[PDB]
Amino acid sequence: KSIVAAAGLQAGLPPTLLSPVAFRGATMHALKARSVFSLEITGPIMPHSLHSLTMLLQSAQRGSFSAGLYTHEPTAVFNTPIHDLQNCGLHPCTVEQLTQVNELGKLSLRHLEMTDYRYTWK
Amino acid sequence: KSIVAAAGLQAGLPPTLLSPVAFRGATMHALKARSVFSLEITGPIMPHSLHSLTMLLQSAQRGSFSAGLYTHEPTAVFNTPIHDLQNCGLHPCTVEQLTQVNELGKLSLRHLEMTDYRYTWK
Amino acid sequence: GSVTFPADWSLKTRLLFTSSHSFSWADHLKAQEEAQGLVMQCRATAVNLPHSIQEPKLSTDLRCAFQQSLVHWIHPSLPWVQLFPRIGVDRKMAGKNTPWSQDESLQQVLMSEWALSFTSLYNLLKAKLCPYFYVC
Amino acid sequence: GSVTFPADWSLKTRLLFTSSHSFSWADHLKAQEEAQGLVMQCRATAVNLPHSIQEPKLSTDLRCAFQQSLVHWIHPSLPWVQLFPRIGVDRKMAGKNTPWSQDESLQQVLMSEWALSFTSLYNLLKAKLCPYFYVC
Image (cartoon, each protein chain N blue to C red):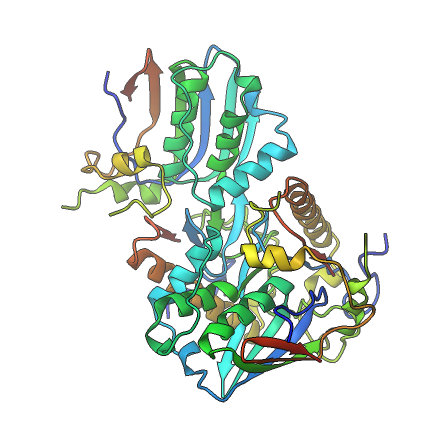
């Protein structure tokens, strides 16, 4: 009885659901991309989208680019460590990356740099 | 400037789009099925749905069932004759059926009967 | 008796199947069956059932194909407004909360989204990635 | 220099890529490329680009993969309301047409649809047909 606010601006509006695959009642959406060299992408960025974008830019930019990530703070603690996915609908490289052990704690990436096909995250 | 009504009950509502495959802005929906023997299915029925339902009921009912179709009248004239679809996302039998020559004119099916794996439409 | 019925391009609104045998197989679908049906529809999987089935209630393929056959896509998602029958339907459209009737910026936003969806649908149709679509 | 960066499970809101070379390949996408990207995303197609590309503007696979990577799914479809950031936003939520705030039957309808979508999403997750999903 406390998921939906009963007083304020967001009064009566049900919670938002995000997913990388379709579900009953889903609505296909797209992220806004705009190039200025620099490239800007805005919207709700999920980890698979970021990994796919890095994979594409690695080949497109010949393994040389820098990225500045703006994070939503109340979701930074999700990195807290906790310890057959072929049909989940993800690239095998993304599945391999996401099946790791959480190293960061209460902290999120703020700057990613790739030089000569080597990653040096900040 | 006449697609959207400017006065009445449907004032400002944009036209509805229906499709058998996903598109930008689509919302996945489902038809209501309820069994009473009899089976009732309600909602916007497109030809591929009807063909798939007949294909399923042929095996399930051992080639013996009868169907009563209620039609939307302002869309009955679409049967007027007019004269590589493997990736369209349809069953090959449905593609074969839909790639025929329109026999009906201004008329729609009102009763379909299948006895001993033979179709006698009314 | 012909093998197949002639193709009908009209839009039905209600179907009633009657048969001597039981239709109870298409009831109480499990969660796994519904999830598999949705995934199969989204991934365009073709299902070929055997010539005859004697135990429909124990056939997962039949129920998954049923759930797959009960799926379509509609652009405007307004759950409290009836949307399929748009011609000659005013009794069911009376007494509803429609903010777009008076506000104009909201109407422009809805129109822009509809235009984008229509353009995307036509582009899908052109590349033979969509058989047909209706505009009501 | 490590091969891969550590996995981040936080939700970013804006990304800015800078590079010496040109990003103009990811602009003026043709209709065919967008349609192919949407279809590829809906059908779970894996794209493996070569080790290096010297003419990105003439590579259809790269642009199709870009359009595929720019697709996600959100349940509530209200085009005139901001929906992703729900915690600590009120300047962007001020002065908007919200009929659900006062009317109660509409709120109940929205709640029922949300419950059905949540149940379907969990059922998809259980059968390993969906990696993860966020509830905000």
